[PDB]
Image 1 (cartoon, rainbow, N blue to C red):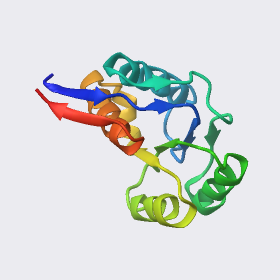
Image 2: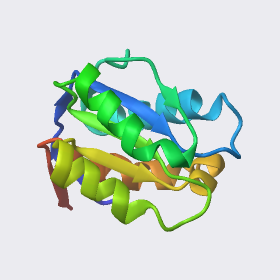
Image 3: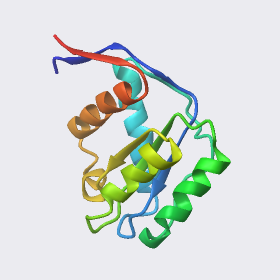
Length: 139
């Protein structure tokens, strides 16, 4: 528990996309609700409402969904991405977000999201802080 945020970024524009078919339809909301609480307890500030409603769509709609989210939310500071159930799409997703559309994303495996492990969300929260412009350290 020695990893801390020196400076917690402030996120005003964020939302969540899920390419997972397997998970309960309430998990994206629940998972993001706790993750943000974990980001916030560690020093970040988050607007509690996403900038556009959460989206759930099939893995074959990756190109479409990402570009849709990007055009409807040009100011997005963060996209929380729930990855497809089968691995192999992560490179495509990062490429589209990071290189092609210019969107800061955090990708999360649906099987791990399902666990709602609080140490996993601690790890993700610190990853999100740096991606969003914050600073982390180890005490």
